[PDB]
Image 1 (cartoon, chains in turn brown, green):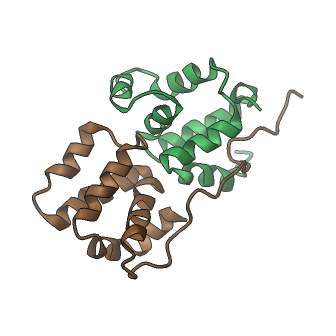
Image 2: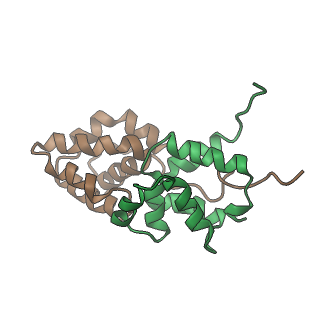
Length: 105
Length: 94
């Protein structure tokens, strides 16, 4: 859901997130241990405001819903009205994804 | 249910969907299971890093499926959980 949404409004998130929004999403990303210091410095070196958000979107390729929802959930605190239709946030309880069902014989 | 109770064919699908979605997936999971982001950075240099995390976690008592599915939520990667809930049905005779 958020993995699809980040590819629907990719051109809106970069225009909505000025620069202070990126710094706040970055602190929140590291709180979930989803980004290593080795690549979290590569998003913080970018000398151009819009180019900062580019390296942030490059991590989303590996992350899927993680670096995606962080954007949708940051913009919620700033209530910019550009992206009111935000995606889901963690709706799984015990779906048939990892769960067992098979047995011997 | 425990992750050690799963059949070998299920564990293969989890490895395939990890390695076919990303290369840091297991690292994020490890961080929220009780490991550290900079500490896994040395673990990525191993010959079987994905298998070693699953093995070193399966030797613990918290190796339950309900906890594993919720541990993807911590990192914010419901994309792994939803991909597996939609990719449960795929096989052929060939």
